[PDB]
Length: 173
Length: 173
Ligand SMILES: [Cu+2]
Ligand SMILES: [Cu+2]
Image (tube, rainbow over all chains, first blue to last red; front, top):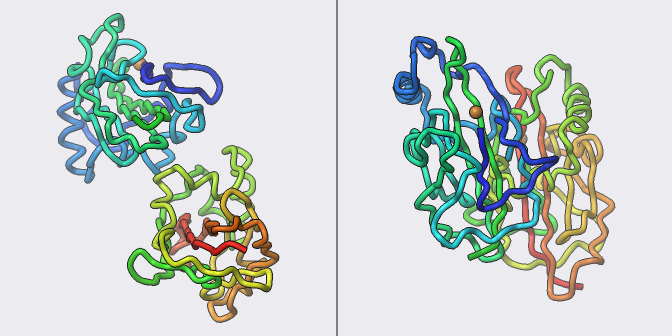
């Protein structure tokens, strides 16, 4: 659960930290065998190479199983100035395994195969900070930050994928 | 397949009738279970209201799943004078169902839910003519015409959406 809090998104309705969708793993495999995050991430790594995976954005964009574009955030909201310290900040700590990435228009500016282990300490209470994030490519006149996170979890023995997506319009830098 | 031929477009590379993207339907539905172009249009109409649809431009602009702005046409191409007869002419007949629209800068000057039935006869050989089109709003010093068409078709039983986009720079009246 969670959303990018800085820079600050607008909301189609109200603020929520919920996932866009929660679905069965879209690639057949031994997901349910894993007792913990290490196993899930290993399965993801192998099965993604079996399924022509590139990145989370290429996986989700254009496929309605992953739910609506931009999730609960509003791409048409008033654009905000990005942070000046080369970061983005999450609304909470990252407590699920799985890959995440930040895009500024068509440029991927941050990516990790396991955002949980890279940007927080795995607890909810320590706020996750994404870094480095270079906003310098943001077109004058403005650009769209997009966050994508595919959380992998085994929920009482049954593995699910959750898709988290934010769109956050920025002013040019 | 096709492009607005009058007024005359310029091309990033070479003239092409092709679609910008071909994607699965972006709204989950009974596309494949319906019959004929009429079934595609009735599904589109009903799912439109489920998915907050306004118009084709609003669907496509700012969403990379619908591919690059202006498609294969060049917005930095040669400015051309608009037709004097209150029409735009396509490069061929229109042989796929679905909505299309013409814009002059931020003004929508023509929209139809099914360009196939409104502007041609369903065959490639009867040149489609869009009408009525009023070019009188074109700023002195120029405007940009934009054409948007979301084609709906079944390809060996599997429904796809295709995006066609043109931009054509016009001289001012
Ligand atoms: Cu969660
Ligand atoms: Cu075609």
